[PDB]
Length: 115
Length: 115
Length: 115
Length: 115
Image (cartoon, rainbow over all chains, first blue to last red; front, side, top):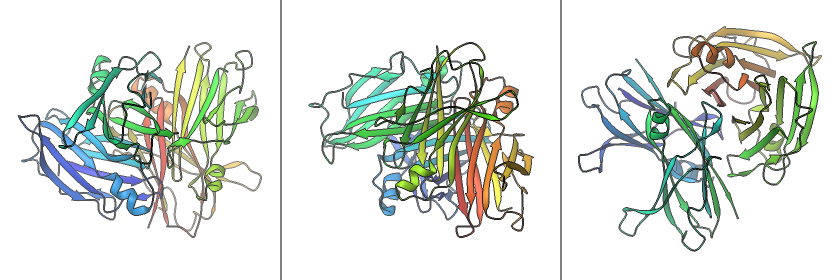
């Protein structure tokens, strides 16, 4: 899959397991159509989201549903979800990994773009 | 203002000046309604966004136009906008400071919530 | 003070109060010599560490006693101390603000350097 | 290896390649003795640092030499190196991965502890 999502839990120092992830692609009407989704594995990773054929250039939104994750651990978080909006570009490297580091009130989202 | 946004540049170690920030509030019909907007000052902070009277309970979206900030520095970044979605004032009125740290391929969001 | 340290709690979204901070300066013989120390205030900031006259060029080590902060909250964290090692005033005198964000298994260090 | 180091470059959105990493263990005299070292691979990862037999409980320091990395990319950084001081504990999970996210003026170090 040209798009992968990896999530780490900075409170427990663990992969963030069973975190729902939703990917949307922006349509011609400037609305977000569902594109792909899943839940992170025991390794905190979500594979198989899409294929090279389906992941064409465009604007994508990745929603990592962090609020539900922290609620299940018993910690009240700040945000509804971590949101990454980005443009997929064919000229750059072929694989996009969205790496999220989560704490309840602070979090980072980084794109590692490789091939 | 009960809502304050601070934007910093992690490449140069400086405040991020003149960055556009748009705040939306989810309406009854689930659409994002415009709420407030402004641009960060020389300190990287955006003050005067709203007031205690206007900033009622709700789901807010803070959109930091950030790709634009980096492109102004000659950097083609990964993400279009930093986006922070949070429920505000659900336990009663609070003061929210959202600090966004900008890197070309990465964004960090931190919220300090006080009384 | 040309050197300011701010400590924030990423689990609770609050300043980190009463955190011990020790600053060292590398001596001619390569040992770390004590330079200044203090404890963060209710805002999470430690002011009054040093002066323009005392903070000369050199290699400085900022040690944030942080494992101790987390252990006081009932959290057994990964790291003993947040540690920031930097050369200061090598291009001339500057003002340094170091912001440390504390999580149990993670620490983030940000420096804002101004004139 | 029970200890692994992974490093990401938030300016380029890439693994941080060829980054020198030094691990020290604290001795009875409170001095840091060299323990293991290496340089990150094309994946930004450093494998084979140690073995379960050699990595006993104690206090360890991981120095990721970030200054040299940013100098080779043409960006003046804040810090001499990212430093992680931590205590290895036999009761917890067996594998420690130190995950570093680097920008020139802001960086995070997280321990992912698994088995």
